[PDB]
Image (cartoon, coloured by chain):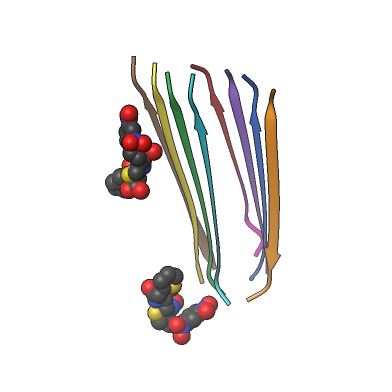
Chain colours: A red, B purple, C blue, D orange, E brown, F yellow, G green, H cyan
């Protein structure tokens, strides 16, 4: 089949 | 000093 | 089982 | 002064 | 194929 | 305010 | 406030 | 023909 994974990381000091 | 990361993965059968 | 991967990194000081 | 790096890799088994 | 993603976030005060 | 982030993405066929 | 980001991508045929 | 991509980002104040 088709699998899509998106990972987003946002960093604030 | 904000950091933004985007990761995209696509699976094709 | 074809694989496509995209990585985006953004850093702002 | 912001730095952005993007790398995309596609491969087939 | 089965693709597995692990995300770890650590923040120090 | 140190931040450590680890992300791992793996594919098993 | 030092920041460490780790991204890992693994592809197996 | 396995492909591995690692991205590391380090920010220092
Ligand atoms: O976290 C780990 C240990 C693991 C256990 C299980 C899975 S991975 N992975 C990395 C590795 O082993 O490869 C570590 N990565 C860093 C970093 O943190 O950049 C290192 C620098 C050492 C350092 C640290 C902390 C500080 N600090 O907080 O000041 C300063 C340094 N340094 O640069 O000397 C090298 S060792
Ligand atoms: O740890 C290592 C060495 C490395 C150090 C750093 C990056 S690799 N061993 C590899 C690994 O596990 O990753 C070899 N790979 C595999 C497997 O998949 O378990 C094996 C089976 C068959 C195969 C499938 C795919 C490929 N491929 O994609 O190239 C190659 C082999 N092979 O015959 O070695 C035997 S071991």
Q: How many marks?
A: 0
Quadrant of ligand 1 in image: top left
Left or right: B12, with H7 as reference point: right
> Where, by quadrant of the figure, is residue H4 drawn?
bottom right
Left or right: D5, with A8 as reference point: right
Instruction: Pinpoint residue E2: horizontal percent, then vertical percent.
Output: 51, 63
Judge whether G10 appears above or below H7 on screen: below
Instruction: Pinpoint residue E12: horizontal percent, then vertical percent.
Output: 34, 20
> Where, by quadrant of the figure, is residue A8 drawn?
top right
- Check residue H4 for magenta coloring: no
Instruction: Pinpoint residue H5: horizontal percent, then vertical percent.
Output: 56, 57
Instruction: Pinpoint residue B9: horizontal percent, then vertical percent.
Output: 64, 52
Judge whether F3 appears above or below A3 on screen: above
Q: Quadrant of the C terminus of chain C?
A: top right
Q: Identify the residue at image location x=53%, y=70%.
A: G12
Q: Quadrant of the N terminus of chain C?
A: bottom right
Q: Which residues are magenta?
A: A1-6
Left or right: H4, with F3 as reference point: right
In-front residue for pair E10/A13: A13
Q: Identify the residue at image location x=68%, y=59%.
A: D9
Q: Identify the residue at image location x=69%, y=23%.
A: D1
Judge whether G2 appears above or below E5 on screen: above
In-front residue for pair F6/E1: F6
Q: Identify the residue at image location x=44%, y=34%.
A: F5
């Amino acid at each position: 089949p088709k699998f899509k994974f998106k990972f987003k990381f946002k960093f604030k000091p």
